[PDB]
Length: 7
Length: 7
Length: 235
Length: 235
Ligand SMILES: CN(CCS)C(=O)c1cccc(Br)c1
Ligand SMILES: CN(CCS)C(=O)c1cccc(Br)c1
Ligand SMILES: [Cl-]
Ligand SMILES: [Cl-]
Ligand SMILES: [Mg+2]
Ligand SMILES: [Mg+2]
Ligand SMILES: [Mg+2]
Ligand SMILES: [Mg+2]
Image (tube, rainbow over all chains, first blue to last red; front, side):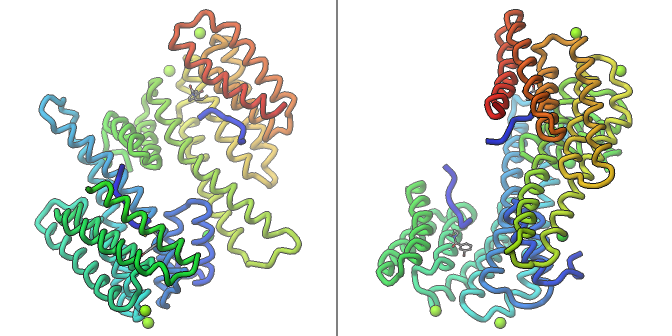
C-alpha cells in the first residue's frame, strides 16, 4: 500500500 | 480476446 | 531534434504517443513544443506533465527495485557479487537525474517566468517541487539538503499563490497539497506536518464542494480521496 | 557500447534489468553478451528471448494502436488531419523493424551457425521465424512475400528438427508449433493449416504427458493450454 501522489 | 503466441 | 517540426504537429503527436503508451516519445514531443517558446495552454501543460511523470515514474520504480537489491547485497551474510548492482543502480539513477534536470530546465527556460495566471504558475511551481523531490529521493551527498530545500521552496511558493488565488477545491491546488504533504512525510521527515496539511486541505475542500457543478465535484472529490488514502495510511 | 563489460557482468545486469522491468536495457546487455562470441546457455537464450520479446512487443502494440488511428483517418467522412498520424506510425514502424533486424543479425552472426544441439538450434530458428513474422506484420511492399517466406522457411526448419529430435511435450517444440500456427492463421492466410497444426500438436503432447515428472508436466500443459486457447478462438 504505497502512499498517493498526484498522477 | 487476442490469440496466443509464445511469451 | 524537434526544431524542424511544427508546434501543432508536436502536440498532435504527443497525443498519439499518449494513446500508444509511448511516454518517452510523448515527452520528447512536448519538450520540442515547449522549446518553440510560446506559453502552454491548460491542455498542453497537462500533456507535458503526463509525459514526464510517466517517464520518471518508470525510472523511479526501477531505481527502487535496484536500490533494494543493493541494500540486501550489503547485509552481512550476503555474498560478494561484485560492482554490478551498484553500477546498474547508478546508471538508472543518472538517467533519472537527467530527466529531472531536463524538466527543471524547461521550467527555468522559460515556462515559469512567463506564467502569470495562477493556474499556470501554480502548476509549474508544483512541477518544480516534484522534480526536485524526485532528485531528493536519490540524493545522498553534500547537496542533498540544498535539493530538499529547493523542492520545499518551490512547493511553498505554489502553496502561497494557490491559497490566495484559487478556491480550496481547485484540482491544481489539491494536487499540490497532496504532493507537498508527501514531501513532508517522505523527504523532510515531518510526518505531523504532512498529516496536518492533508487534513486541513481535505476539510477546506469539503466545505467548498457545495459551490461546484457535478463535473467539478467529481474532479475535486477524486483528489480529496487521494488525501484521505494517505491520511488512512499514515494514522 | 558493451564491448568493455565482462560477459558475466552483462548477464548479471540483464537479470537485474529484468527484475526492474527495464527491457530495453535487458536487450542491450544481452546483445552485448551475444557479441562476446561464445555460445549461449539455456538460461542465457531465455534471457535474450525475454528481453527482445518485451521490447518488440511494446513496439507492436503501439504500431497497432497507431495503424488503427491511421485507418480510421482514411475512412471517407473523416477530416483531413495532415501527415502526422502516418509519420508517427512510420517512426514506430521503423524502430520496430530496426529491433527485428538487430535480432536477426545476432542470429545470423553467429548464433545459428554455431548451434548444434536441437534445443539451441530449434530455439534460434523459432526466433528467426518470429522476427521475420513481426517484420511481415508491418510489411506492405515488394518484399512482403519474401519476408513471409523467410519466416515460413525458418519455422519449417525448426519444425523438422523438433519432430526428429525432441519429444512432443518439449516446451520449445510446443512453443514453436504455437507460433508457427499463429503464422499460418495471421500471416499466411492459412487458418485450416493453423488449426490442424495446433490440434495435432496438442494431441501428440497429450499422449506423451504420461512420461513426465510433475514439474515437466506443468511446463508442457501450460503451453498446451495456449494451443487450446487458440483452437477455441478459431473454431
Ligand atoms: C486528478 N489529477 C491527478 C491527481 S492530483 C489532477 O487533476 C492533476 C493532474 C496533473 C496535475 C495536477 Br496539479 C492535478
Ligand atoms: C512457457 N513458455 C512460453 C510460452 S511458449 C516457454 O517455455 C518458452 C519460452 C521461450 C521460448 C520458447 Br520456444 C518456449
Ligand atoms: Cl551498468
Ligand atoms: Cl514522427
Ligand atoms: Mg504569460
Ligand atoms: Mg482565482
Ligand atoms: Mg556449438
Ligand atoms: Mg532429443
